[PDB]
Amino acid sequence: DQWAQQVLNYGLLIVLFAAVFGLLMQIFGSYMADLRFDGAQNVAYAIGG
Amino acid sequence: ELQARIAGEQAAIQNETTKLQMIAQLRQAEQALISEQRRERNMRILSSGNQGMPTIQ
């Protein structure tokens, strides 16, 4: 019973982290890929975001 | 005549001395201008009038 419970625990962990981490890390990657130190973007806005 | 020729030669060397002083002043001015351009670029990057930021899409 305990072994099955731990298997379920870590399976749910891997599912949740796969999905949510992929989504969040892709969003962060896109945002950082748009970042530029040109004269047109506010440095404070970009770093704060 | 030779004395006056040598005097003119001294005047020419004086003129070169003045020219070298002028060149040194111009060198200093050029360095100051390069620094001014650097600071203009820095101000342009960090200006608070900028309104852009990355977009989430």
Image (tube, rainbow, N blue to C red):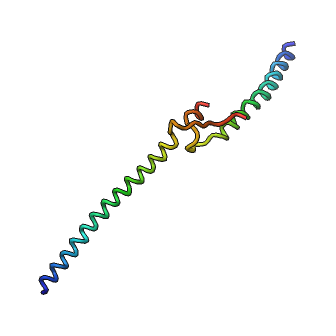
Residue A12 horizontal side relative to residue A47, left or right:
right
Tell me what residue is drawn at x 51 percent, y 36 percent.
B48
Q: Is residue B49 above or below residue B19?
A: above
- In this view, which residue lies farthest toward the bottom? B1
Q: Is residue A14 left or right of residue A32?
A: right
Residue B15: % across, % down: 23, 71
Residue at 48% over, 44% down: B42
Residue at horizontal 66 percent and vertical 40 percent from the top: A34
Which image quadrant is residue B53 in?
Answer: top right
Along the viewing direction, whichever of A8 and B10 lies nearer the viewer:
B10
Image-based side of A30 in relation to B12, left or right? right
Query: Which quarter of the picture shows residue B54?
Result: top right
Check the image and report above or below for B2 versus B54.
below
Front residue of A42 and A14: A42
Q: Quadrant of the N terminus of chain B?
A: bottom left
Question: Where does the image place residue B45, in percent across and percent down from the top left?
Answer: 52, 42
